[PDB]
Amino acid sequence: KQEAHRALELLEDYHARLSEPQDRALRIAIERVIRIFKSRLFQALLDIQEFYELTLLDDSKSIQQKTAETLQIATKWEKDGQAVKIADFI
Amino acid sequence: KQEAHRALELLEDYHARLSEPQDRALRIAIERVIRIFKSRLFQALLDIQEFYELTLLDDSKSIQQKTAETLQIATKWEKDGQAVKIADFIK
Image (cartoon, rainbow over all chains, first blue to last red; front, side):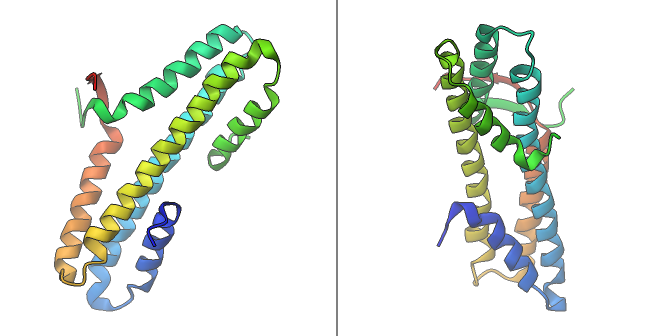
């Protein structure tokens, strides 16, 4: 139970088993959750891809510079639980 | 290539090839990226697990109430997905 790596798998399976017409509104709402979650995951993975490209693959940057940039990215992620993040900002 | 689903794999491979002593500080910094990224993914997965438990598994909630809750969590997560950081507080 509650194997974190399976969380999305289980949500998808719950969706698949929701096949009665009186349950259809819930089914469509869960599809929206699934889409939104996979978009979050995709953006996270692009954070890695963009770091890999801007920093690690750029042979013009010194090891020192690459190290600094590498530390900076992880610090941002580490601080996100205490971050003030404003939806639909100016 | 840049296939998103393999982005962490490629980073793991770069780490593995970064074996010279002058590059060791960068290797250790990359270990920290990998650790922190995995924590981010775990926490995201727990956001699903927590919704699944609280809403979908609770047979005492009507389909209507589960639907309402599911819609609200999508609205919230959509706002979160585009929110911009302005500050963080120590602690």
